[PDB]
Figure (cartoon, rainbow, N blue to C red):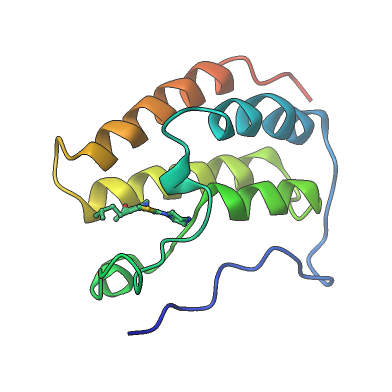
Length: 126
Ligand SMILES: CC(=O)c1c(C)[nH]c(-c2csc(N3CCNCC3)n2)c1CCC(C)C
């Protein structure tokens, strides 16, 4: 079995910015989810080899995880907050696509997503 290359976290020819919204996404949103008791399955790319999930990357073609998001934020990879919000939403959606309703992993994603929504509700104006 093989894992794919992880999502990129640096791309020198991609234009980058540091906005107050992106700062909030790191200092408030990511930090809140990262410290949560249910964060651990989401802190690095899914290791389909070790988890014995050979179909994971057959079903999930746009993988995303908080380790990737954290590095993107720390490296100022994004142009705007919407790009980063999309990454969080991709991460949650992938979990719901792959897994079964009520699975532990889905309950974990739901708990993190609730906090995400609470924090994004107060995203500052630019
Ligand atoms: C399939 C799924 O949606 C999953 C997601 C987002 N995460 C995990 C998971 C478990 S353990 C771990 N890591 C990652 C990297 N660092 C080591 C610990 N990730 C899964 C598998 C759940 C179940 C189907 C076996």
